[PDB]
Image 1 (cartoon, helix red, strand yellow):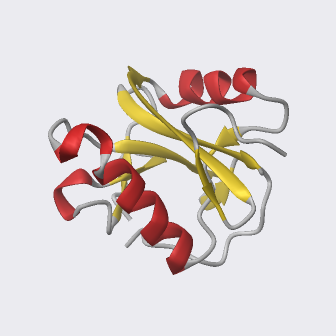
Image 2 (image 1 turned 180 degrees about the vertical axis):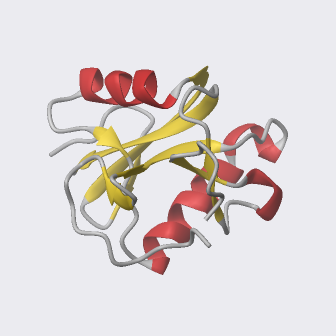
Length: 130
């Protein structure tokens, strides 16, 4: 199926980057509204991780870079994907504080993931099947 306009098509999924700074739950609502079946992105392989990082880094020649919400959230002490997919691959290193939602970390060129407070405003990335 054709990807939404401007979305990256990579190995059977589509990825849409949004530089609008929203709290995690609003970001997730936004993604769901774009297309049925879309959610904040899950990342299941290093190659997918690498492709997403490249895609975000090319946004505006890499000038505007900020942390980017993904679909990993902590609940009942466990990290999981909001899209319901199984978690295996991870680039998230406790922070036993109230930081229960994950971002791609800009300062590492989106190599590492970090946990942020869910009410923090960040850019975000959506994913749907291609």
